[PDB]
Image (tube, rainbow over all chains, first blue to last red; front, side):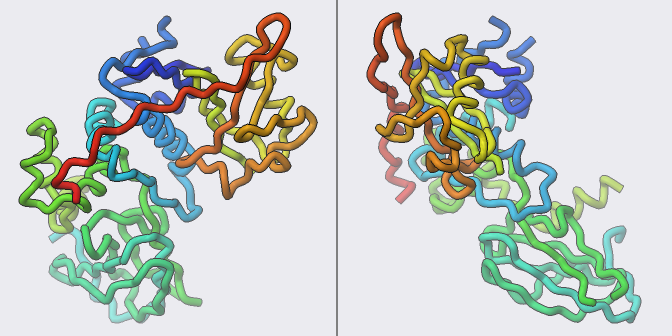
Length: 88
Length: 142
Length: 104
């Protein structure tokens, strides 16, 4: 039910599998097959990615007003690169 | 042209509620299928609108043209009337697209080329959201 | 009402949700399921403040306003090794690089 995503700087993010599987890339990387290492994505980026999964799963198929997903300017470039690689 | 308003001449009253943090640009598809811009709604605001049954509307960020939803879908079609509600909301953008929006909003288009990013991301940045494109997309899906 | 949390210890971070009306003890059960350490070996914190087992997450300050999907609230976690509890330690995330000149 939970999987571990490890950042370049060694941070270990434990998220529900269904949340992780909103990345196609991660879905493929799971096929310690419940652990995945990201030697190119630092913790300040991977933490945001995980927040995005929570966000996506909460608000996908919701009639409630949906809030903006916030992204600080300082991480935008890296988050872009990570999002692109992760396909999410 | 496949995506067009029907010329019904049947009045239908509608409320456009901007339940988004963006300045909303309402867009009416005319009888030829040409997008027609109407007045902008600032964030949080509403307008009572006289339209007609079978008319097609969609909604976009007025500054960046990012796609918005309306009653959780792409197109709004006034039905028979009580005013009908058109709740305009953010979609759940992909993280990639949201990142693009933020980067676009922070960098002048002539400086995209000076970002230390792979070529294919320059191009992804340059490929701004575009109504006529979205309409070609939607037309082919039929 | 769901509240969205990061449960954080050292270099570990769990993303989960829980009910506002659920208890600190019930959360330790969630952590137990995941990290294989039982409630009596866990201390949970909000900031530097130790949280009481019988208190709701709401009573502890985790609410829909403060513990959002896109911006979860942090819960500190500390383990007991045999005798006594370690201090609460949370390794910060990495720093982003300086903002490129073209993003001003």
